[PDB]
Image (cartoon, helix red, strand yellow):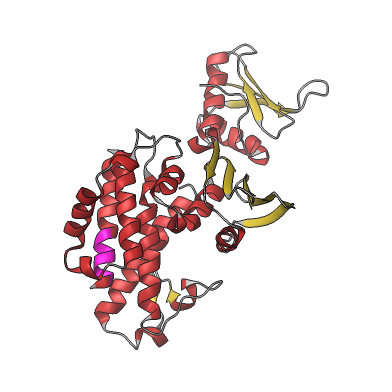
Amino acid sequence: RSYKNLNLVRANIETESRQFIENKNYSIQSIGPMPGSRAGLRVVFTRPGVNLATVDIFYNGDGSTTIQYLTGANRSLGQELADHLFETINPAEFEQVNMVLQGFVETSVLPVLELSADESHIEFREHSRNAHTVVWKIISTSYQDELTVSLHITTGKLQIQGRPLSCYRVFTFNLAALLDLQGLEKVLIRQEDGKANIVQQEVARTYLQTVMADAYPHLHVTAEKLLVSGLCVKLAAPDLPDYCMLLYPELRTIEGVLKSKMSGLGMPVQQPAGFGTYFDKPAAHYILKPQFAATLRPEQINIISTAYTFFNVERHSLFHMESDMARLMGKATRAWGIIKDLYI
């Protein structure tokens, strides 16, 4: 474990430290700036019976923070604070993305950016433009995250660089329905040489037809392709710490099938209000608004409400960073039941 160059929320470090120290019934000797001109914070704490732990917390010029507990008189104690602070960080913050997707033009990219900034914690700026390259920044100031998205106009190459955090998650979610199997695989597994392309599509297809049952022949072509590609990605997925993004094909399909269904019941879903203009939210589940529910059978109301609720809760959990494969499969199975019911 390295405590160098961490992406800590600087304004939260002292509070997190004091809370950790209080939870342990340790005592503060001091918390304040370091000697001289050194940038950062020094925390000195202890408890009766052992010596003082000094933890030096260096603020680096790039905005990251390096924790040094290998100093002072009580390093085993200081390491407890270092690990507390380390464990405040989402594991994904330690990953890097720098990928290129082929076959993109500005009129296809721009709507994805605009959709993405419909999220409350997401904004984007056009960072630079010339005849060869347009560069955009997607920014979550809330979380401290920024993603650089560059379209190389003359080659059609769309480059995504940063970390796989909230900006990446929102952008790739909205990009996902445009991508071919290989692109979709790249954004979901974040690796360069995936094996989805060697999965026998007809076998996967048969799996899907089995789950969809009665709904299968009513599946929209676009929904069937997204689900089957997604199934290939799950089937060839490498060993990952987290498989949650492998639920993107299901969630995106629900979004499409659901919009299509409520538009067909005279409830068109339009940005920027989105689904919100149709739902009220009681407890942990959403329910349809009376003006709209009045036009529907109770069954329709229930399927639509369940679908929107599952979509919203799972997606919110993904966009806000909140057996592993078996758990994922439980979620995907549920999502397939939902899609099926949407088709009735």
315 or 193, nearer to the observer: 193
Q: Residue furthest top?
A: 73
| 203 sits to left or right of 147 | left
- Within the image, what quadrant is residue 124 found in? bottom right
Outermost front residue = 154
Q: Is residue 141 above or below residue 285?
A: above
Give the farthest residue toward the right: 36
Residue 83's place in the image compared with 153, above or below, is above
Residue 149 image offset from top left, x and y in percent: 61, 48
Q: Is residue 169 above or below residue 256?
A: above
* Residue 340 located within the stretch drawn in magenta: yes
Segment colored magenta: 336-342
**Residue at the image position 64 percent from the left and 13 percent from the top:** 71
Please state which of residues 126 and 134 is positioned toward the viewer in this rendering: 134
Query: Who's the residue at 38% across and 49% down the image?
Result: 181
Q: Looking at the image, which is closer to me, 177 or 274?
A: 177
Q: Main secondary structure of the magenta part?
A: helix
- Which residue is painted at 57% across and 47% down in the image? 157
Tell me where residue 90 appears, x and y as whole percent: 50, 38
Residue 337 on image: x %, y %: 24, 62
Residue 326 placement: quadrant:
top left
Q: Please give left or right for residue 19 compared with residue 230 in the image.
A: right
**Residue 170, how many percent across, how many down?**
52, 54
Residue 55 picture quarter = top right
Residue 283 in sight here: no
Residue 267 appearing in the image: yes
- Residue at 27% of width from left, 42% of height from top? 199
Whether residue 297 is in magenta: the answer is no
